[PDB]
Image (cartoon, grey):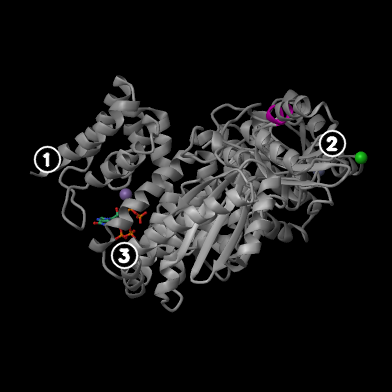
Amino acid sequence: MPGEEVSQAKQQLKLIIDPYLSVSEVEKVLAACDFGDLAHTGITRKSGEPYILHPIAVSCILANMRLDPETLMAALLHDVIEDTQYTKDDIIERFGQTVAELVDGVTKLSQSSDKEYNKAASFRKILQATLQDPRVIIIKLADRYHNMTTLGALRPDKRARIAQETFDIFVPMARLVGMNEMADNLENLCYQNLDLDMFDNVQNALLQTKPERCKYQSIWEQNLAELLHNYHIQGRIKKKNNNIELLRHFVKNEMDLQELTHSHAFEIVLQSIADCDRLVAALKENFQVIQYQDHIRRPLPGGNQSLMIKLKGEKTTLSLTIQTELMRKAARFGVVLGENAPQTCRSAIQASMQNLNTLTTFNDLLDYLHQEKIWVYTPHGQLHELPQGATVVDFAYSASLFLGNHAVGAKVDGEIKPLSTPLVSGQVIEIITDVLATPNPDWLSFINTQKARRALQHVLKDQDIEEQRLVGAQALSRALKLFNRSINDLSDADWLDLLQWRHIDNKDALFEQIAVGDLLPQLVANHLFANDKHPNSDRLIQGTEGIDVKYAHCCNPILGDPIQGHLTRRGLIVHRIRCHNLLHEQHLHPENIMPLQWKADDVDDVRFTAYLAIYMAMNDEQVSDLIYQCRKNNAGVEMVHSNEQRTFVNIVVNNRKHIAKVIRDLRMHYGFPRIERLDAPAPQMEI
Ligand SMILES: Nc1nc2c(ncn2[C@@H]2O[C@H](COP(=O)(O)OP(=O)(O)O)[C@@H](OP(=O)(O)OP(=O)(O)O)[C@H]2O)c(=O)[nH]1
Ligand SMILES: [Cl-]
Ligand SMILES: [Mn+2]
Ligand SMILES: [Zn+2]
């Protein structure tokens, strides 16, 4: 009976994977089910059934979406790392590096009930994890979905905070990745736990009026078929489910059983844009227009085109989405559950992230997305998002100037740890202060945040020029200790490289740049000891380990572009090698310019935005075809606009090689028009 429940659930998963997975792939997925069963032996859920029944049910949801074996294995083991004695290394052993990273990723999106729930921070963290590997968010959405269905076993106190997090981030996130059925199901379960009484009243009315609503939807499908025929418009009509739109409305509105019965939604697929406008004109003649949105002339972020018109005919209300056969096909590039692999959807997910905006917050996210932060907490549960490699001092300054300036030590998870201790995500940090304490300048050696570095440089701003050179040497000697080296280990050849590399003449002047200038002692150490035993390699730019970097908005450098960094009081700013802002500051201060190289010419987990100016006028059908051609080439369409002389397109590409392929494919498709790549978006569109 207890083991027999697990076996009949495992057998139900086998039926789903047997048709589409290979014999060896099915054995690997079923082996993960046996290992998950072993890790959770004896553990039972709040309802009483064995724990493994949950990841099995989650893996069944994913197997029904025909997802890859790694996704299914990671879902079956996503709770064995934290809830069990088993570790990430155990998973790397039995199932490989890919499933371990997926399990790790899903685990990172978990919200502790005793820690702060910050909507904006969680949105950023989830968006970052999604763009790093979209499979992680699909597993997490399936996990959250299964939890929402069994929320009855949890206390009504708990039921609210989870339904709120699901509603605030998971529902928008599932729509973003094209999992609209999942998003609707999640939103339904959110209403069930956020307003049970109003939910039960609306659901019962929906259920009682369901057969009558079917009858009238069939009537209106025929009336719409007749209308298209009368106006000589060729098109297809699809009946759409409108249960979530009706529930969403009547949960906040007074009940009108006639409005609930006679409200229908349809999708109309036409042959051309001229027919779309012709149908809109025809509909206006026969109905009263409630709402109209033109997403053909103004396409949605991501590139989605459609005409959304809400009509009223007496008791009847119709919600119609009208689009061409090409628009419907373009929309199926970027959906994580479509023909394309979820990972190829990265560009589409990132281009359409402008659809989530709650404030211009999802406007300048590039630095955050490419550089995973650490999530450490105050003993009160307060979140602090810090760069990778941040020490206790960085946390102290992040909390406040008082705590940073007067810090003497810290208690990490109850254990006393010194001020240079690098932090790890999930740690609770208690800064120990002394009102008589003064910040020590030697902290610069391990400091990686700008709030901490600037606050320490204010103490050296009133110090002796000789003492500054000493502090700079003290900070460089400690930065070298990370690689088992020191200043006495530096040969004359090592010093000669540093002085030439920093456009400087003496050793004391290099120390002045570390102590008072904007040269971080970590960048000096990473240049002398390159790619050898540096203590999650998130780094896209070589030698920037332990420090956070920023992309300049003047030139917007993309992976693969020749780049050069600029050392400022805000950190290191990455610019394209021929940016006019960069060359201006290189002429004035060549010592503040550091040459930079991208670690790998083609990293697949990152996406950037390229700005294009196509020297040709494009009509409605040509713009629609341009969006299609971009999306078909795994490049998301962030924005398109066409005047009578040019057509601008902001496109989300992987690297400089990808944008070269897109430009080359667009040129031969359009009869070789001139296409120029801009440094920043044109003022005609935004800017
Ligand atoms: N809905 C439901 N949940 C159950 C049941 N039995 C155990 N749980 C677990 O309760 C957890 C709820 O998370 P918290 O809000 O942190 O509650 P907690 O502090 O008591 O763990 C879930 O962890 P999780 O999967 O990691 O989700 P989460 O921690 O990301 O919310 C879920 O696995 C049950 O019968 N129904
Ligand atoms: Cl020009
Ligand atoms: Mn779980
Ligand atoms: Zn620049």
Q: Around disc 1, counting alpha carbons within 10 Å, would you say few (fewer than 14), some (14 to 19), or many (20 or more)?
A: few
Please identify, in this view, whether the residue under mark 1 or under mark 2 is nearer the observer: 1
Please identify, in this view, whether the residue under mark 2 or under mark 3 is nearer the observer: 3
Q: Are marks 1 and 3 in contact (CB under 8 Å)?
A: no
**Mark 2: amino acid:** Ile
Horizontal and vertical percent position of residue 167: 44, 61
Please identify, in this view, whether the residue under mark 1 or under mark 3 is nearer the observer: 3
Q: For the point 69% across and 52% down, which residue is it?
A: 277
| Mark 1 CB within 8 Å of ligand 1 | no
253 over 154 or under it: above or below? below
Horizontal and vertical percent position of residue 543: 65, 34
Q: Quadrant of the N terminus?
A: top left
**Mark 3: amino acid:** Leu
Which stretch did the figure color magenta? 656-660
Secondary structure state at the residue bearing disc 3: helix
Residue 658 is one of the magenta-drawn residues:
yes
Residue 379 is one of the magenta-drawn residues:
no
**Mark on residue 504?**
2
How many numbered marks does the figure carry?
3
Secondary structure state at the residue bearing disc 1: helix
**Mark on residue 3?**
1
